[PDB]
Image (cartoon, rainbow, N blue to C red):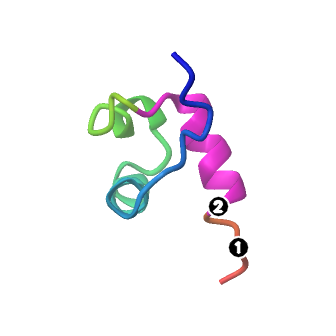
Amino acid sequence: MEVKKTSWTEEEDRILYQAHKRLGNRWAEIAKLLPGRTDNAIKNHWNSTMRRKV
């Protein structure tokens, strides 16, 4: 394994947002929709990418 550049994608980002607001912040139940996305990466993503200052 040597992916390294494990960048996200439109679908994942959208699903993450649509899920997060519905579940609230139950990352365990949100990742149920995205098993290929671990909590660490999800939150890291939710903290780094989504916080682009809307």
Horizontally, residue 40 falls left or right of residue 15, namely right
Is the residue marked by circle 1 packed among few (<14), some (14-19), or many (20+) residues within 10 Å? few
Amino acid type at circle 2 is Thr
Residue extending farthest to the front is 2
Examine the structure image and report whether residue 12 is included in the region drawn in magenta. no
User: For the residue labelled by badge 1, is the local secondary structure a helix, a strand or a loop?
Assistant: loop
For the stretch drawn in magenta, the main secondary structure is helix
| Rendered location of residue 38, percent (x, y) | 49, 28
- Using the image, determine if residue 2 lies above or below residue 10: above
- Using the image, determine if residue 8 lies above or below residue 50: above
Residue extending farthest to the left is 33
| Rendered location of residue 36, percent (x, y) | 37, 30
Q: Give the residue drawn at x 49%, y 51%.
A: 8
Q: Nearer the viewer, residue 4 or 33?
A: 4
Which region shows up in magenta? 37-49
Rendering quarter of residue 43: top right
Horizontally, residue 45 falls left or right of residue 24, namely right
Q: Nearer the viewer, residue 23 or 4?
A: 4
Examine the structure image and report whether residue 44 is included in the region drawn in magenta. yes
User: For the residue labelled by badge 2, is the local secondary structure a helix, a strand or a loop?
Assistant: loop
Per the image, the residue denoted by label 2 is: 49
Q: Give the residue drawn at x 33%, y 28%.
A: 35
Rendering quarter of residue 34: top left
Per the image, the residue denoted by label 1 is: 52
Amino acid type at circle 1 is Arg
> Marks 1 and 2: CB-CB under 8 Å?
yes
| Rendered location of residue 29, percent (x, y) | 34, 33
Horizontally, residue 7 falls left or right of residue 37, namely right
